[PDB]
Image (cartoon, rainbow, N blue to C red):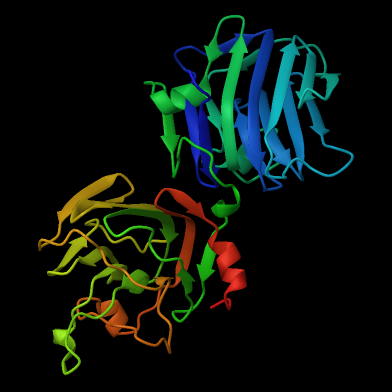
Length: 380
């Protein structure tokens, strides 16, 4: 066993079914560690009506609410000097024995209080949500509407009878555990969860050149409601002759991801022909998030959207994507010297620029803070 982690991006949650083995306890413990930059997000919740537990971040404080039917306990713990949404790990330990609740943060202090009136037992037969839920704001005792945005690890709920290793069950899988959204079982950078909006077709960023010619990967999440747009594009040095006078004569190693008429396509040329692939059958301009993953070794690889994956093999005997200079996200520059427009990229031929959100971009498995890039590079 190593530590079990996940990343939550605002629409991600775990759900554990409690119907077959519900909770009737007089003693409880909840432990986990969180890392975040958002002031508000549900960490976990478990009751549906009279009895409930809700642990959340509210205005940078850790907020715990526990009601056993006769009335609630509620408490917020926060440093005198600042907040807990500081992109640092924090451990939270929560214990409950009959009516007495205790919460310790970062093994620093312990706060102890009580639930009201007479009831002594926590009952929940519904769901155990981690990181979010379908409607967080309707959860009883919830002080937040937002789902978690950051990393959670080592989420564990135990009592005298049951121990639910909820992070573990998430990764490894269980008939009673269902997980939803764009979940990676890893924590890289919390800063990168913040989306970037391309508000007009003309807006775009220029990222760094791709690390190697022979292999590469690129992955990212996108959300969009427009039918056409150039999401990603890069090309090499031109291979046609100087006395070439027709755009069909253009020869250049290029890579592109584009949307046309609602459908998402990958386009790639390695020196010997252009291959073009409808990355998924359905239209993806419905405003929902999609995860995009592209893997390439030589002239073969894969392009995944969500969990549909598609293999591809490029023509030719060259195994090298000989990319040059810049890689463009969200559109193209107006006055770039030596910019080449392949004939197959209809998006670039018609100047369709992307409009939508991109989030959490990865090149060669290394996370990239595009926000730093956006602020630092012309906001367009």
